[PDB]
Structure formats: structure tokens, C-alpha cells
Image: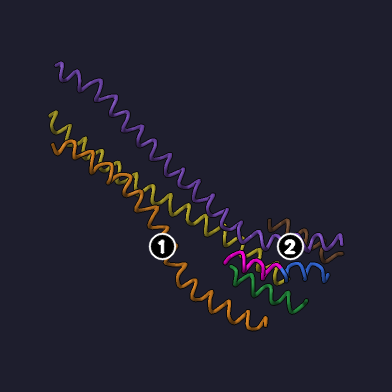
Chain colours: A brown, B orange, C blue, D purple, E yellow, F green
């Protein structure tokens, strides 16, 4: 949960 | 399989960037050489009305 | 050729998503 | 699975990036080509300013 | 004086198209730098996400 | 960038 929430925030910040 | 991937795709990417430099230089030279045409090929035939 | 390389990369994307 | 929807976004954004870098660079160069077109269209308007001017004045030099 | 004013008009018109084309070449380098810079920002983000 | 992405896919495949 915490890793893929951190990946979502990283990836919206890459888009 | 994936070790064959890492060593195959990267020696290809070395040969591909040895061509991507030529295709960036030709695309850069298109934009410039067309800006050269935009003045020179207007002047050329316009000044042939005046050659007469 | 870019679609075929995207089919290759797409298996490992959907796998590393699912494997979380 | 609420986390897999984020792993799928991170996997799809990597696939997307392979067209997105071309879409960005094409839409950059198509804007930049419209920008070199708009400076060169104002050069057609300068050369029209000279054309309306030589039409008005050099025709009246021929009347002169 | 009208013939000199017509020769300097050709020099004006030629040198305008020449410097408009060199300006259009500098804007073409500016636009090619953008389309490489849009790739570099995307390659940096893809690399950092892939590592993490 | 298909290669730069594929080297990153192999570090993901090593996890998978």
C-alpha cells in the first residue's frame, strides 16, 4: 500500500 | 533470456545513437536550409521578372 | 517495430504491478 | 488492488512515454514551424507594405 | 538618386530575407532543443522511477 | 529509449 501510493505520487509527478 | 536482452538492446542502442546524431543534424539543417530557401527562392524567380 | 518493443515491455509492466 | 491500479498507472506511463516523447517533440516542432511561419508571414506583410507603397507612389512617379 | 534609392532597396530586401532566415534558423534550433529537452525530462523521470 | 526502458524492465523482471 505505502510503496504503490508512493509510486502513484512519483508517477503523477512524472506524467 | 533477460541477460540476452540487456546486452543485445544496448549494443543496438549504441549503433542507433551513432545514427540518431545524423538524423538530428539533418532535421536541424532542414529547419535552417528551409529558412535559407524562404529568402533565396523568393528572391531568385522574383528577380527574373527584373532580369527581363 | 516500436509497437513490438512496447509489447515486450508491457508484460514486465503488468507483472511488476500485479506482483506488489 | 487499490495499489495495483497505481502499479498499472506506472506501467502505462512508461508505455505512454514512448509516444509522449514523440508527441511532445512533434507538437514542439509544429509550434516552432508555425512560429518560423508567423515571423515569415510578417515578412510577407512587410513585402506587402512595400507592394501597396510602390503601387501608390511609383505609379504616381509614372504619372509624374 | 532614384536609381541609388532602388539599388539600396534591393540590398534592404535581400539582407532582410537573409537575417529573417538566420533568425528563423535560431528559432529552429530553439524548437529542436525543446524537442530534445522534452525527451531528456522524460528519460530522467523514467530512469529514476525504474531505479526506485 | 526502448533500450533505456528495456534495461529498466530487466531490473523489474529480476523482481518478478
Quarter of the figure with residue C1 = bottom right
Question: Residue F9: percent from the left, percent from the top?
Answer: 69, 73
Q: What secondary structure predominates along the stretch shown in magenta? A: helix
Q: Is residue E34 above or below residue C4?
A: above
Residues at circles 2 and 1 in contact by the CB criterion of under 8 Å: no
* Element at label 1: helix
Q: Residue at x 68, y 63 (%)?
A: D14
Chain bearing tag 1 is B
Which quadrant would the N terminus of chain A be assigned to in this image? bottom right
Question: Residue B5: percent from the left, percent from the top?
Answer: 63, 79
Reply yes or no: does residue B4 show up in magenta: no
Q: How many marks?
A: 2
**Is disc 2 surrounded by few (<14), some (14 to 19) or many (20+) residues within 10 Å?**
many
Q: Which residue is mark 2?
A: D10
Give the extent of the magenta segment. C1-10
| Residue C18 - label | none
* Element at label 2: helix
Residue E52 appears left or right of B34: right
Q: Is residue C12 above or below residue D40?
A: below
Residue D21 appears left or right of E3: right
Q: Which residue is mark 1?
A: B25
Question: Residue C16: percent from the left, percent from the top?
Answer: 77, 70
Q: Residue at x 33, y 32 (%)?
A: D46
Chain bearing tag 2 is D
Amino acid at each position: 500500500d505505502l510503496s504503490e501510493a508512493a509510486n502513484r505520487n512519483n508517477d503523477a509527478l512524472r506524467q | 533470456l533477460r541477460r540476452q536482452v540487456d546486452q543485445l538492446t544496448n549494443d543496438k542502442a549504441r549503433v542507433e545513437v551513432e545514427r540518431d546524431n545524423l538524423a538530428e543534424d539533418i532535421m536541424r539543417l532542414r529547419e535552417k536550409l528551409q529558412e535559407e530557401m524562404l529568402q533565396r527562392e523568393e528572391a531568385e524567380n522574383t528577380l527574373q521578372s527584373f532580369r527581363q | 517495430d516500436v509497437d513490438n518493443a512496447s509489447l515486450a515491455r508491457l508484460d514486465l509492466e503488468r507483472k511488476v504491478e500485479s506482483l506488489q | 488492488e487499490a495499489a495495483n491500479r497505481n502499479n498499472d498507472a506506472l506501467r502505462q506511463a512508461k508505455q505512454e512515454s514512448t509516444e509522449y516523447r514523440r508527441q511532445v517533440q512533434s507538437l514542439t516542432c509544429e509550434v516552432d514551424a508555425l512560429k518560423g511561419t508567423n515571423e515569415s508571414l510578417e515578412r510577407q506583410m512587410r513585402e506587402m507594405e512595400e507592394n501597396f507603397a510602390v503601387e501608390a507612389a511609383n505609379y504616381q512617379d509614372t504619372i509624374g
